[PDB]
Length: 48
Length: 147
Length: 146
Length: 49
View 1 (tube, chains in turn cyan, green, blue, purple):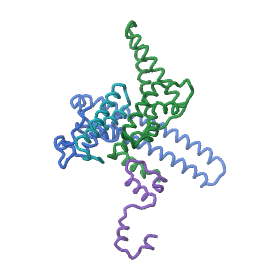
View 2 (cartoon, each protein chain N blue to C red):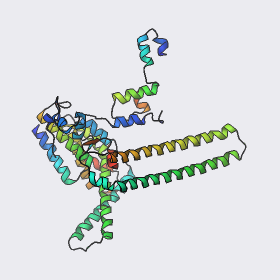
View 3 (cartoon, chains in turn red, orange, blue, brown):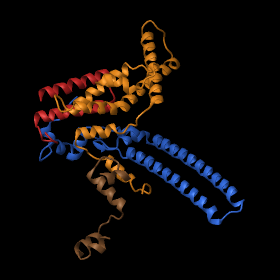
View 4 (cartoon, each protein chain N blue to C red):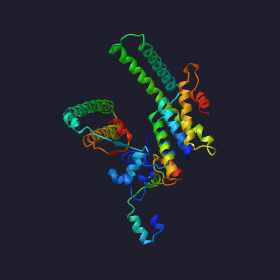
């Protein structure tokens, strides 16, 4: 879970630094949020 | 039927849906951009070339240049913004090719969404390194970078 | 980017929802990038310039009316051409009325599309008029228009 | 056809009279728009699904 969160955060920061479409950036942010929720309470929202 | 407020309200209600699954929501978002063809992609590449040329000229003029008036600067700004917008449009058009290519590597190591985002990164790289002068369809070149 | 805490977002009582007076569905839609939320509105300056924005909306509506009247004049000219090609030569009354009914359906669907455009314009203007903080708007097309 | 085949069932005949959804195409549209949210229903997609 920690590795997933790190990967999503690093990819998001790389995307925002490089310049990406807003829909791609929003998808990456949603993935990062889902990873954080999975790390804290896995399976609380959606499938675990 | 197709008219008289028969299916438009249903389509609007469907578009206003949660779609709690993240991958399903991403597919819904990616489905809102129509595909392109050879003429569209070559025109977009021309816009990219113009925008990059204008940005390079602006960077050159920034130091050891001239005080650009409003008339001479607004054109450069407008063409730069047009080029960036065309690049974004091409990215959103080819995201479908990205996901179609990335569907084949699921089930080992990482997740479907991670593969999709890596595909978008590869597509960005391909768009940066694309060359329309070769007279080639964009998918053939972008497949290598996505992979 | 900041991320909300699942403990305080999702639960039997929604702590964040109670704090912000927002239902859990709205909270989920805002958090998981499914819709937009109006963070703040400039009430004073909006009320100060409401006259000017109302004038701009009125002139846009007026331009819509002139272009729709231009389409009406064009369809009247098309009807005149149909009359010239129908009533000036020998043919069946039902045959000459079939084209009339086809034209009538074409212009009625054109006017219906104009009505949908009118409804969308009025919806945009009203949403601006009664915009409020922490208000959720779905259908990002409306957000882009605003 | 429904009333001529399933006629003795007065309870669901009354349910039918309270269907508030007439038309085969309308029925397919309702079924599609419910079981498949988020997608735009079409004439053939409903039948094929």
